[PDB]
Amino acid sequence: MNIFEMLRIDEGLRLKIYKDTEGYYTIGIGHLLTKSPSLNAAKSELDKAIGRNCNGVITKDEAEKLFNQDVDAAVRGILRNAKLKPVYDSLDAVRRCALINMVFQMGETGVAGFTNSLRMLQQKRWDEAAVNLAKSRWYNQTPNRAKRVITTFRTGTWDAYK
Ligand SMILES: [Cl-]
Ligand SMILES: [Cl-]
Image (cartoon, rainbow, N blue to C red; front, top):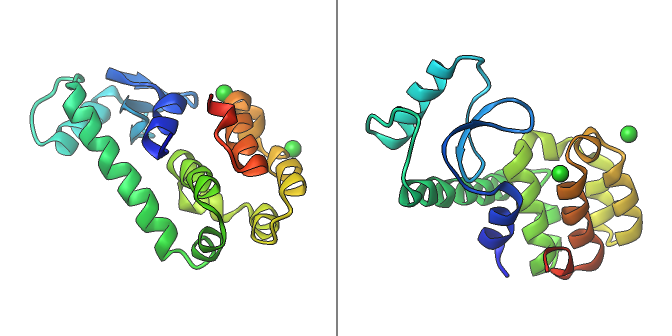
């Protein structure tokens, strides 16, 4: 299993503008378009993203293209971030996927806000980091996904996804 497969499980795939768990306009594989209430602001962001007139709908190829860009951007952001980079470098391959997952869903900033959990992952205190990660809005708002990512951190295997 790889990052793409993991995130595809967590975000699903939709070819028409949709609202995410938070009520924000999204398309494809978790590609956030806008936080603006306007469906028109979304359609416009969509056209800009695709470079064509989409009218709120895209093909699977287009969805996958956006997906490739988003994962690449997530990874490059972690590698450029002073707070994230060191955690990342310290982890094993599977657990690195889990940090990418969080950054994809919640942005660099968000993640960088989990100070204490980050410190615990760095020290490799798995069970304790797991407990701390759960004490978050993230866990309360999307418990099944959070559980999956959290289990990945705790065990270092893909069991939660299998
Ligand atoms: Cl809490
Ligand atoms: Cl969930």
